[PDB]
């Protein structure tokens, strides 16, 4: 056996962003940034050909909803790309299509920022302001809709993934 090491910390809290125009000072309430570096996940209907080329881009870094509580409660275009600590959250998204695997620094830990008592706390969300560059997307597994399971012989690694710890 061996015990795991601690995580590298980038000076820039949105180092991972695919759209660097995001304005960290407009995030409300004051963000509590994730400091761990385990695999995160994102259920998305968008296909890997697109995600591996572009990364995850947010809907609207300019005029989107920068208030995290508002974004979480009432889905609206925002500067954030949502991910989760929970490998299995894809089972709750119908027509999910894909479970993406993400190894990215930072992100806003939603429950540490707005509390763990709101309606969607069990999503254990990490919100990435400005999204996530493709170099931080490990890969993807397609999801079988009828059983809500991963088609594990059809997982694909992202050729652009760059390990960093
Ligand atoms: C960037 N938009 C396409 C995303 C959207 O409007 N909703 C959305 C779309 C996909 C999402 N996927 C997730 O894995 C997730 C995990 C924790 C919390 C939220 C999500 C999530 C939310």
Image (cartoon, rainbow, N blue to C red):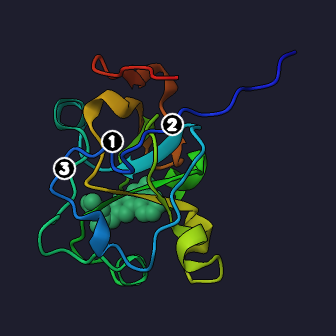
Q: Is residue 123 toward the left or the right of residue 139 in the image?
A: right
Label 3: element kind: loop
- Residue where numbered disc 2 is placed: 150
- Looking at the image, do the residues carrying marks 1 and 2 touch, with CB atoms under 8 Å apart? no
- Residue where numbered disc 1 is placed: 16
Quadrant of res 102: top left
Count of marks overlaid on the render: 3
Up the image or down, 128 lies above or below 11; here it is: below
- Residue where numbered disc 3 is placed: 20
Up the image or down, 102 lies above or below 106; here it is: above
Image coords of residue 61 (percent x, y): 17, 64
Pointer 1 local density, CA inside 10 Å: few below 14, some 14–19, many at least 20: many
Pointer 3 local density, CA inside 10 Å: few below 14, some 14–19, many at least 20: some
Q: Earlier in the sequence, mark 3 or mark 2?
A: 3
At a point 58% along the width and 51% down the height, the residue shown is 85
Q: Earlier in the sequence, mark 1 or mark 2?
A: 1
Q: For residue 109, say whether it is visible.
A: yes
Q: Distance between the Cα atoms at labels 3 and 2?
A: 32 Å
Q: For residue 93, say whether it is visible.
A: no
Q: Quadrant of the N terminus?
A: top right
């Amino acid at each position: 056996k061996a015990a795991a090491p601690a995580c590298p910390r980038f000076d820039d809290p949105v180092h991972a962003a695919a759209d660097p125009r995001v304005d960290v000072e407009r995030i409300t309430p004051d963000p509590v940034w994730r400091t761990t570096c385990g695999t995160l996940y994102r259920s998305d209907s968008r296909g890997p050909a697109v995600v591996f080329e572009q990364g995850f881009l947010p809907k609207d870094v300019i005029d989107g909803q920068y208030d995290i509580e508002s974004y979480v409660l009432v889905n609206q275009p925002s500067p954030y790309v949502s991910t989760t600590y929970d490998h299995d959250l894809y089972k709750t998204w119908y027509k999910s299509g894909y479970n993406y695997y993400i190894d990215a620094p930072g992100g806003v830990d939603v429950n540490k920022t707005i509390g763990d008592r709101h309606k969607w706390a069990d999503q254990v969300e990490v919100a990435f302001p400005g999204g996530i560059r493709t170099e931080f997307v490990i890969g993807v597994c397609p999801v079988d809709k009828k059983t809500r399971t991963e088609k594990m012989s059809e997982c694909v690694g992202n050729p652009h993934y760059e390990p960093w710890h």
